[PDB]
Length: 91
Image (cartoon, rainbow, N blue to C red; front, side, top):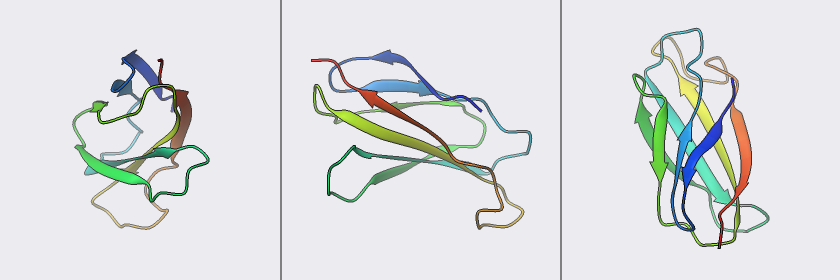
């Protein structure tokens, strides 16, 4: 799987990823300021989608963004390998 920022502004972005081979219940999107000490933020995206908007970001900051797939067949790392990327918002 390959995650990418397809559209962005200094304060928000649109991410897109490849759906895994398995049926997904939902995805967990987590994001945080890279090298920051605040708790990561998290939101859910329905399993039928593969894009999501992230808002409330700060301009010119590096964020670590990760997607996790959760299946309705058992929760633990036994769902789907996380996909992550580092992306710096423009100024």
